[PDB]
């Protein structure tokens, strides 16, 4: 009997259909505790303590964990982040320079904290010129509603909640084009991978299989009503927002997974960790993170 705790996050993306369908549990035979986390920092803590065995991390929390030598490996990509993550601001902030002196919320060390710092650098704004505050996404929504922040760099469901009355100043497709791309990945603890390698393979299979029909034809996938409703329920967003969110990333075929896990992910961790170090967020980094990536489960 195998028990596994999976830390998941709120991005509306096609693999959530397999989560809703319980496919990983059914195919693997394991009892699966799917636990929602608000952002990647708390997932890193839970992976490090052993309370979570498989977790969904943004590339920035991944780089923090790898720099701390947490015994985890990326074993598949979830998505290449685009405008599903965005900087949404009060409508009177009209230009990047208007951010000076404003209060902008991000969950610390998340991909949107990272992207905010990369965007400020691109715009020639020192981070200390902005009051960057640490809040988790539910608290960001509450602070926005009360007028206590001027904007936030967020993912769903906060990004769409804020965009209802706000303006998108930049997004992670643009920030990626500026040279700071971000990813969402799935990681596994070494001790779990050692003990239950076929369960890890079953997790990868369920996620990869679920994304392929979307990749093959996005519009056909999006018109199957149960695909929309499953993502709306698990992400906590209205059905009307699901298509724009799903199209706000790209996803990987099995061939792309193997290719990305054999070099590109390592390079992504190296570069992400180095920028975090330059920004003062990690004290020390390595020139190689191959211990933190594997293609053996895809």
Image (cartoon, grey):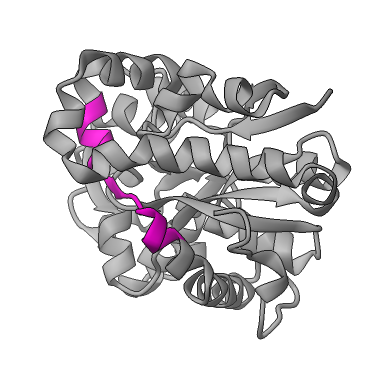
* Quadrant into which the C terminus falls: bottom right
Q: Nearer the viewer, residue 148 or 4?
A: 4
Residue drawn at x 28%, y 14% is: 226
Q: Nearer the viewer, residue 283 or 147?
A: 283
Q: At which x and y percent is residue 223?
A: 14, 22
Residue drawn at x 81%, y 54% is: 190
Classify 258 as above or below 11. Answer: below
Classify 241 as above or below 285. Answer: above
Classify 165 as above or below 291. Answer: above
Classify 239 as above or below 61. Answer: above
Does residue 42 appear in this view? no
Residue drawn at x 25%, y 45% is: 215
Span shown in magenta: 242-257
| Residue 245 is one of the magenta-drawn residues | yes
Q: Which quadrant of the figure has residue 15?
A: top left
In-image side of 69 versus 239 (left or right): right
Q: At which x and y percent is residue 39?
A: 58, 38
Does residue 221 appear in this view? yes
| Residue 57 is one of the magenta-drawn residues | no
In-image side of 50 versus 75 (left or right): right
In-image side of 188 versus 211 (left or right): right
Q: At which x and y percent is residue 231?
A: 36, 22
* Quadrant into which the N terminus falls: top right
Residue drawn at x 64%, y 75% is: 277
Q: Which quadrant of the figure has residue 192?
A: top right
């Amino acid at each position: 009997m195998v028990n596994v705790t999976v830390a998941y996050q709120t991005s509306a993306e096609p693999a959530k259909v397999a989560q809703a369908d319980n496919t990983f549990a059914k195919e693997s035979g394991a009892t699966v505790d799917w636990r929602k986390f608000d952002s990647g920092a708390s997932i890193v803590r839970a992976l490090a303590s052993g309370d979570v065995q498989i977790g969904n991390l943004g590339s920035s929390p991944l780089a923090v964990a790898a720099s701390q030598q947490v015994p985890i490996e990326v074993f598949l990509l979830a998505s290449k982040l685009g405008n599903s993550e965005a900087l949404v601001v009060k409508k009177t902030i009209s230009k990047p320079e208007d951010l000076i002196g404003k209060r902008i919320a991000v969950p610390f060390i998340s991909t949107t904290h990272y992207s905010l710092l990369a965007a400020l650098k691109h715009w020639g704004i020192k981070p200390g010129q902005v009051e960057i505050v640490n809040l988790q996404p539910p608290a960001i929504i509450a602070a926005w509603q009360r007028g206590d922040i001027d904007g936030a760099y967020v993912w769903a469901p906060a990004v769409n909640a804020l965009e209802k009355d706000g303006k998108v100043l930049t997004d992670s497709e643009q920030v990626g084009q500026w040279g700071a791309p971000t990813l969402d990945v799935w990681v596994v603890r070494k001790d779990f991978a050692e003990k239950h390698p076929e369960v890890v393979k079953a997790f990868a299979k369920s996620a990869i299989d679920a994304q392929q029909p979307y990749i093959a034809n996005p519009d056909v996938w999006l018109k199957q009503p149960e695909n929309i409703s499953k993502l709306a329920r698990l992400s906590g967003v209205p059905e009307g927002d699901v298509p724009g969110l799903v199209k706000g990333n790209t996803y990987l075929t099995p061939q792309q997974q193997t290719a990305e896990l054999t070099g590109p992910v390592n390079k992504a961790i190296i570069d992400t960790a180095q920028f975090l170090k330059e920004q003062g967020k990690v004290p020390a980094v390595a020139n190689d993170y191959s211990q933190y990536v594997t293609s053996r489960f895809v």
